[PDB]
Length: 213
Length: 222
Ligand SMILES: O=C(c1ccc(Cl)cc1)N1CCC[C@H](O)C1
Ligand SMILES: O=C(O)c1[nH]nc2c1CCCC2
Ligand SMILES: [Ca+2]
Image 1 (spheres, each protein chain N blue to C red):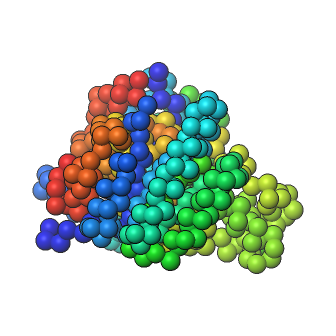
Image 2 (tube, helix red, strand yellow):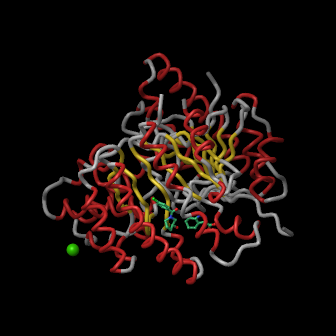
Image 3 (cartoon, rainbow over the protein chains, first blue to last red):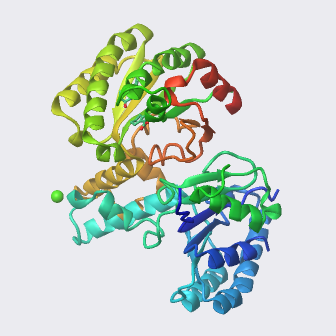
């Protein structure tokens, strides 16, 4: 194994909670990782008590505001995936501002999955395809993997080749089901608040074959 | 608590053949026998559904001689399983894109599923010419065909509606997924069905996989 190719698209399930991301985003830029996608808020997280949901909405508003100057300083594109119909209007307006101000940035793409689920993503892709059929734009017999995949979120980015799950659990928990179909899976007992750039870099090297698990 | 639906990625056949200095394809030949005690263990312990990744969408791009051996092994397996399904009261199912399989193998699959459809102790599913992406896109094609017939309003498509078109929708969700062979990957298997499944990865190559380790994997889930 002479050539050690790092992942092109890393996805992270940031579990173990019940500022960590900034040095990880900076390490992606340093090493040439093109995309980083993080699981901030799941479809399942709407089932938590209202005060918990309200607190996560405040943490999300806070994180985006703090990220916008960093995205501009480092020329990183900031994107969001998930169902926005269930989110507060001002948070949606903030998400739109962030993604519109950074859409042309080419250093890396940081995607934050908010009110997101792999199943929701897939069924939404199916809905848009069926809408195209209803509007007479396409015939349903043309629907195969090649057509359908274009409607799944982040299809323009490379496939997820490395999925990191912190917090000790061995599950994908309805995250990027489609996009991570061939991703190498890295599980760690390290809780998200304790997750380091040293361990993030080790996960990258496990993927490349430079380091062993 | 026992898992309701166990899925297995039976990897490591070729590595086993190389490790034990066997002939080309012998890993698949030895590997074919490993599932029988597992299937019997599932029935006797009360596992309701077992789904195995016998041939993937990606396996169509393997060397042709390997595709040939796998097609012959599938045909051999199905014949051998039909009397076993009748004895153990197991319903045998197949999932995957049948349009890509040999016509005679599809007739044999149809025979096996029809003759065992009334069995109710367990459901054994063999994923043949299968990929989670294929399954998902096929479910989207079927939803869109219903839209074209005027049966469904496209604006109404959501997770609850879509899930009904994905394979094994009448079975519980996969709650335990086992992968042998040392790789940490789902490799386009039951992407939808295993969305919340516990994952058990092992270095044990599939031909070396035992009922004892499988039983330990059930214990780990509980
Ligand atoms: O591992 C198996 C198997 C499946 C189901 C049963 Cl019941 C037994 C073996 N197979 C099927 C034949 C060829 C496949 O590649 C591998
Ligand atoms: O490539 C291998 O070594 C291997 N191990 N088990 C299987 C395969 C390929 C076809 C499905 C079952
Ligand atoms: Ca048509």
